[PDB]
Length: 277
Image (cartoon, rainbow, N blue to C red):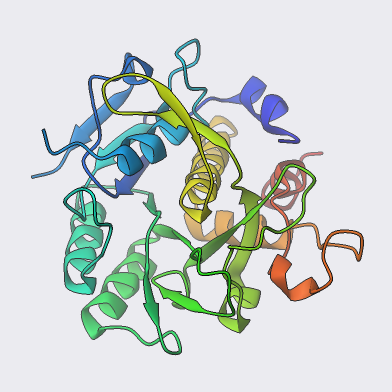
């Protein structure tokens, strides 16, 4: 991933920056969280949730190289294991809880498929709560391989995240759609290494694993603002991430709309957010 090392050389996270992971129960005994600052809000262990959290918080030198290892983390489980289906009511409650506990970024590596992006009004209010408190919600576009919308990824003010491979081309499974043209970027989502409950690591593919990468970068970017004596501003960070996305040329896909607003571009994100090149 271009720019990630240069960014790390400036910061690997700041404890003053909190990222909430709304997913399944995380295996807190995994070696990759040794030294990580994690709290779970009020056996049943999730592979999906452990993997996702490890992508963000995996301590360097552990078996997973997390994007933002020194940041504060909140685990706020939104499903019991095995099935990954999500009540909109429960999600809105988790978001509400994440906000009141001082999360700056909220990661949602799940969604619910909808006919046209419509949402339960309590979910809509949860996103409204985030807008009012300057919390950035970042969510997976989904893996239905169609012009299809998930909530909350399709909701206004949310940052939506699809998947690309290593050649920077969009994958078949990654959802696309007009709501996503407005607010989505592609991040790596093929064979991402992360933790497995009980202690191995596994490579997995999906928008579920792209999303935590953008979450981590957004946290790095907020930490970088602190480093520079600027106020951390997650809504500023969203637009920098979107404005810096690099569009796909015709040697990437046939359909240029499968790329959304474009590809995650860390160096340009820094440039757009701060002064720096």
